[PDB]
Amino acid sequence: KSLLPKKEINVYIGMSEMQVKWYQKILEKDIDAVNGAGGKRESKTRLLNIVMQLRKCCNHPYLFEGAEPGPPYTTDEHLIYNAGKMVVLDKLLKRIQKQGSRVLIFSQMSRLLDILEDYCVFRGYKYCRIDGSTAHEDRIAAIDEYNKPGSDKFIFLLTTRAGGLGINLTTADIVILYDSDWNPQADLQAMDRAHRIGQTKQVVVYRFVTDNAIEEKVLERAAQKLRLDQLVIQQGRAQVAAKAAANKDELLSMIQHGAEKVFQTKGAFGTMAEKGSQLDDDDIDAILQAGETRTKELNARYEKLGIDDLQKFTSESAYEWNGEDFAA
Amino acid sequence: SLLPKKEINVYIGMSEMQVKWYQKILEKDIDAVNGAGGKRESKTRLLNIVMQLRKCCNHPYLFEGAEPGPPYTTDEHLIYNAGKMVVLDKLLKRIQKQGSRVLIFSQMSRLLDILEDYCVFRGYKYCRIDGSTAHEDRIAAIDEYNKPGSDKFIFLLTTRAGGLGINLTTADIVILYDSDWNPQADLQAMDRAHRIGQTKQVVVYRFVTDNAIEEKVLERAAQKLRLDQLVIQQGRAQVAAKAAANKDELLSMIQHGAEKVFQTKGAFGTMAEQLDDDDIDAILQAGETRTKELNARYEKLGIDDL
Amino acid sequence: KSLLPKKEINVYIGMSEMQVKWYQKILEKDIDAVNGAESKTRLLNIVMQLRKCCNHPYLFEGAEPGPPYTTDEHLIYNAGKMVVLDKLLKRIQKQGSRVLIFSQMSRLLDILEDYCVFRGYKYCRIDGSTAHEDRIAAIDEYNKPGSDKFIFLLTTRAGGLGINLTTADIVILYDSDWNPQADLQAMDRAHRIGQTKQVVVYRFVTDNAIEEKVLERAAQKLRLDQLVIQQGRAQVAAKAAANKDELLSMIQHGAEKVFQTKGAFGTMAEKGSQLDDDDIDAILQAGETRTKELNARYEKLGIDDLQKFTSESAYEWNGEDFAA
Amino acid sequence: SLLPKKEINVYIGMSEMQVKWYQKILEKDIDAVNGAGGKRESKTRLLNIVMQLRKCCNHPYLFEGAEPGPPYTTDEHLIYNAGKMVVLDKLLKRIQKQGSRVLIFSQMSRLLDILEDYCVFRGYKYCRIDGSTAHEDRIAAIDEYNKPGSDKFIFLLTTRAGGLGINLTTADIVILYDSDWNPQADLQAMDRAHRIGQTKQVVVYRFVTDNAIEEKVLERAAQKLRLDQLVIQQGRAQVAAAANKDELLSMIQHGAEKVFQTKGAFGTMAEKGSQLDDDDIDAILQAGETRTKELNARYEKLGIDDLQKFTSESAYE
Amino acid sequence: SLLPKKEINVYIGMSEMQVKWYQKILEKDIDAVNGAGGKRESKTRLLNIVMQLRKCCNHPYLFEGAEPGPPYTTDEHLIYNAGKMVVLDKLLKRIQKQGSRVLIFSQMSRLLDILEDYCVFRGYKYCRIDGSTAHEDRIAAIDEYNKPGSDKFIFLLTTRAGGLGINLTTADIVILYDSDWNPQADLQAMDRAHRIGQTKQVVVYRFVTDNAIEEKVLERAAQKLRLDQLVIQQGRAQVAAKAAANKDELLSMIQHGAEKVFQTKGAFGTMAEDDDDIDAILQAGETRTKELNARYEKLGIDDLQKFTSESAYEWNGED
Amino acid sequence: KSLLPKKEINVYIGMSEMQVKWYQKILEKDIDAVNGAGGKRESKTRLLNIVMQLRKCCNHPYLFEGAEPGPPYTTDEHLIYNAGKMVVLDKLLKRIQKQGSRVLIFSQMSRLLDILEDYCVFRGYKYCRIDGSTAHEDRIAAIDEYNKPGSDKFIFLLTTRAGGLGINLTTADIVILYDSDWNPQADLQAMDRAHRIGQTKQVVVYRFVTDNAIEEKVLERAAQKLRLDQLVIQQGRAQVAAKAAANKDELLSMIQHGAEKVFQTKGAFGTMAEKGSQLDDDDIDAILQAGETRTKELNARYEKLGIDDLQ
């Protein structure tokens, strides 16, 4: 049946006033590793910490302790307007629900789904959730429930690496990657919970990216690895074809090539029909002239195919689901 | 400075005698040639026709009972019975004319026997390596052919025994009487002359029987070479996709927008304009545009950029 | 939706008189290694030759009656599996069922192709040498409502990912893969989400020959894969830290009784602050009793009964694409 | 012969003073106790409650301002204000009466400080390794308690302090005042006295505050201990999931004698002869499904101790 | 058919003003220039001396208070106080004369701020991307410059800015005002115009201050450029050593001497026929040993490599 | 100290009549796989069997059951003249002992070392033996016995496996590789049991090769892998230098370059001193011509170097 192609749209988001303060605080508390304008010997382990904190900052400041306003602690509108992605998500969901669409929301951090849980309840959004800490008995009680006709649910919160292989939520039509994995195929699996065999509508995938921050550069580094995986796949295709021996169909065309022309011939063949006896070097000059012409033509035919045009036997893309399931 | 070698496919026809045997091989197994028999059949039946058709495009005397009956004599008939022997004779006479020396490779040592009788009949000085030739013996043939002021002119070799790392740059023309299914095997043969130590332009002539089985053998071996150089070309692809990020890649990830972050006193761009749906539908509109250009910019990229 | 569990039946098959001659010839041509004397490379050749004999003698060159090679009933009665297959397929067609036939050897599908033509069986084929556009042409031509095709020949390691042939309800494994996970992929081309009828899988096994022994070793590795799965689940749960809910249940435990308590709590209330030896003997007696009962509850939890979060099993498909 | 140790959970209540402090700890943050607030709250708030309840189940004097007002004395209130101290006092008394010596482990060093004041109050000779104790100190502390005819009686340690392989077999009783979150830690503390060189039966008493937080803590550790055993017992599974010489030899030899015996066709073929009516096929499928059930029901029930191939099996002879 | 790119180092001197600042920098830190600190002292002190000399080789106005005192008016002094501006001024003039369009890259955006002022003073229509430029902003700059009938003539870029795979083949000349420490960064810049779509000959000009720090930087980049190729060239060697013998190798191994073996009815050479015999074998054996090693220990990766199509055994050459 | 380089000499050896019969029989017992092919799945495993049997024949016919003249067995000269390598070994050892040299003999097959033991006893040669899989303490006992001053031993039988164990056998000066390992580094690891720090005399290594047989063809393939190991080693060194940042000494050379000439200059520098203004396009052509000239010269210096230089 017709499975409509997925719309992958990067939606670039800014940062709240609070996010900027923490993003600055993260960079300042370890500015020597950031600057690289001195020794530049500083270890990568120190940078992996800076990267991880800046990714939490792009998601929500409340993941940092001491960020959220002191007592009284309450779930109000500040849970949204203090995170750029929450503001965009809040209005994105408001439009999504009115058009009769249901959305799966994925994330790298389960503690972010916790924020989304408080958000979903605060707005009256019916939801389900799979962490990878939620059991299979409870899994099937929610995924296989979520799909049921007349469902009360609207949002389904999952971690990108929940692991569920062959779990199908085609009754939802929208996929939101709140944050992105460093392995694009991990995000591809999360998409292929709705964009797989069983889906009847157009699947749209929104990938939140904090513009002009670390998340924008990661997106550009993700496209490289995603592109390089295609080259590795294509190189594998050329390797198999180069290692392939001739089949009887390949052998038959070689035997049959010109066999009728030989059966038709009753005198000499080709060049020997031209002369046969060793005549002028003008004949050799004509052959070497015609041979060099056909040689360049042969080289042009195969020098113009190249990678990315290699014949497709298996339909594997770097831009479709691995088939592997991912657990954190 | 080593000049790039010129390679020319010499498309050659067959003599009247070759056509008789070529039809004989096709007829005595016409059921297989017409595409009959079980799909389960062992590949031996078609591969047997291939070797016979290859032996025919080479020289009919490879078949028993072909050469004019007893007694057997070496005359001009050793030449005018094979389309390749005709072209080779004039080509050799013209190669010796301009002062060039030649290496002649072949898949079949039973053909180098025919080329041996031809060299004696024409009075050509020569050396020969079969693969049945021993080590010290094929060293002497190297030294004899490479000696300054060498009496020898032709060097007969098998494509098998040629590619070992040896040097024969005292010859500047290579003649591949027939081609190997493995493209590198012929490439190694050309590199006996086209390697460091060569002072002149190496030229390679590849005898190919037009409109016969060797013309299709050529296309297969040419494809596999194009597949080969694509894999080698891509070799760096596997490890670059495995690599954990460079420390300078990490630094660029952290430094991305650090200035604009510090310059801010309020919030960043999107939060600077709570926003109306006028903004969200305009944000999604501009977002898809940036995605399209990003994917298009990278999808067409080769590995040299990456 | 309801997906009926697959019925897997081993069909034990004998060998024709021709197979016995070759099976003996293989064992005799290297009886030295069969006897016991060190390189497994010599044995790995014997194994592969015996598998070919269990499949079909015509895979050996010179076995089929000499030229011309005619396709008749001898293509069937010279192979034990072919005799069973011809009558099995005949019954399969009569009950309105369509069958996917897998094999490890593409040259065996070549034999099955000649069989299908000899019997008038419409077929399709995916050899792992089949173009994508040629594969999708065979998939659709077999699945289209009111299709004329009846048999679909595939290699077990054809490597098609997510291929859907749910319009067939019978899968026949002509020979078995050394990795049971590869065969489970071939089954899950008919037995997958979309299947409406009862999937029956017939696994041909040459009885009292090498194929019967391979069948037993496959079940051992199949169970060992299940044990690794269970060790993984038990490992993940063992390193897992407490949830906010798990910490909460620890804090809330007995909190009501403490708020309920005005004076002292438990042991200090039962006999306060000064304990004779009769008091200690009662605590230690009940304490050792509750310790044994507590250990017994946890000593009964084996690997085979672990809290599964993801529901993988060595007896279902890995999702792994087996393109060899 | 090393006797298997006796591990006993001794379930203890709380004094009137502990109930007051236990209630205050639950009251000062009753919102988190009832599971209120957002699900986004970090683990820090609940874990702080766990710490306070753990200290309260140990001894109330771990909270400042708990011990009876100034001036401060060390008397019987140090025993009767904590339920674990009351049980320990008669337990230690009975231990010395039977000629036994005891190792007392704890998670908190501030509790060993309380136990120090107890040991001086009752006149017990003791040693102490803290984990905040220098290397040469604990060496002398080990030797002091292990000296033949040692004056000491009680050895106070923290469950982690000493390090691997230290030997305290001159004691035969181990008292875990409070338990650890990972069961290997407590298990290593028992094996300070339960190891080669121990002559007498090692008995381990584990103090557990019944109907409070420590009983619920204990169940989790007992679970994590049971999980570890299943992993370790199944550690042979991945290395088993190649082919031995005998495995390859058995595949080829299987039924080979019956093949050499056969002159015509094999089983299914000799009895029926390449022609099969419906009744013959029906027997083939009924026999196979029966053999299939018995085969699967035999292997899907097995365990690692049956699948594991000994390394001596490769010693083909 | 993509034409190979002309790469030319154009060696330039310094104005009188630059010689002053080049001396002032070396003077104010004369001890480190003579090498004063111990091995423990970090590279920061010397690296800073390097950057100041780099800034001095580009334009003196990169230092504060260098340009003639306020008010700061853009005139000819902006050009004739920097040796590279003097060369660029006539080179751009000739480039536009023959209808050629130029990409100018730089390591420092503050110099692009100077080239920004130069273009206005000369009336050059231009674009600019810093990497501080937004995605949508630099996309529009890409399209504007690549527009058919574009008004722009110069494109100002920082060497790292653009990203990966942007196309600016609507220009044909590349000018690297100052070089990168990493050779594959300047190489990336040239291939923004030297790539698919380029119809004309791409000329690459690299400003190199002769007898200064940039002359010595130029050599180190070319060395790292050579080592980059040698490691790419020998890249397949690791896969070649892992390779197990394919069918042809095993077949040729078995077939070696088989014909002569079957013909032999007695024994082989040695056994068919003294210590004069053994001394002759060791003598002839060392002779055969030297030649074999000399042949192989000179070989390279082109010869020793096994192509992928080698594994696809089709047929024997002789049967 | 002075460690004289090792003499590595291939000793090309023929085959006895008995070897020829078995070598023919091995090739004949599966000739269809040899001359032609089977399935690509079948042929490769089928050929690997032929290779292993052909090497056993090149080593000794008695490795095959029923080959040795009809049992009961006996150690005579027949144990020697029935294997080509044994005949060469018999006369080499006779010369080796008289020149006051002791020899380590390596082999891939312990059943061949079993043959060598019976040979050594048949000739009266005192020996030791370390077999692949010999107990560690027993494995130490032979090293000490063979090396002890005034040792009685003359031959040391080893498997190439038990060579690379960090053992030191410098009291011997001759190494005989009865047969060769497929991994060239394994044989090279066997030579360094005698040719290492502690050796005072000239180490000579004899590598037995059955000429015009499979062992001669292996010699060519093994030499290729030996060169490929050198290329990977060199790629690693070139990779480190490319990854290496500048030294404090490297930076010092960059700062000082031309600094004295700058201090020497009172006006403007080379191009600006020659002209200095916006002058003729003849001036620009003079720079660009010399610039293209120096670029061709600059690239030429570094395009000369190769993976074999790195200096």
Image: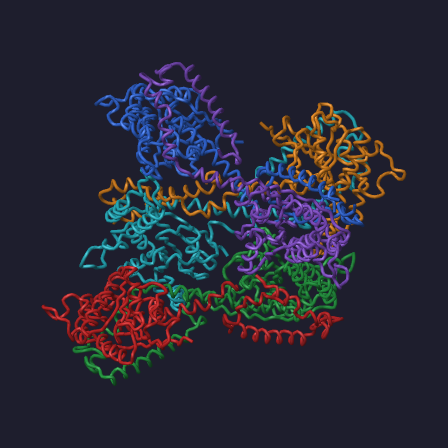
Chain colours: A cyan, B orange, C green, D red, E blue, F purple
Q: Position of residue A111 (x, y in %)?
A: 31, 58
Residue C73 image-quadrant placement: bottom right
The percent position of residue A161, horizontal first and vertical second, equals 40, 57
Q: Is residue F183 left or right of residue F55?
A: left
Q: Residue at x 64, y 65 (%)?
A: D249
Residue B286 falls in image quadrant: top left
Q: Residue at x 60, y 70 (%)?
A: C10
Image vertical order of residue B85 relative to residue D104, above or below: above
Q: Is residue B171 left or right of residue B237?
A: right
Q: Residue furthest bottom?
A: C278
Q: Considering only vertical position in the picture, is F4 above or below E73?
A: below
Q: How many marks?
A: 0
Q: Nearer the viewer, residue C127 or B98?
A: B98
* Left or right: where C213 falls relative to C65: left
Query: How far across and down, in percent of the image, does residue C14 sit?
Result: 68, 70
Residue E314 visible, this angle = no
Let me know if residue C192 appears in the view: yes
The percent position of residue D109, horizontal first and vertical second, equals: 24, 65
Residue sitting nearer the eye, A7 or D29: D29
Q: Residue at 40% x, 77% y: name it.
A: D3
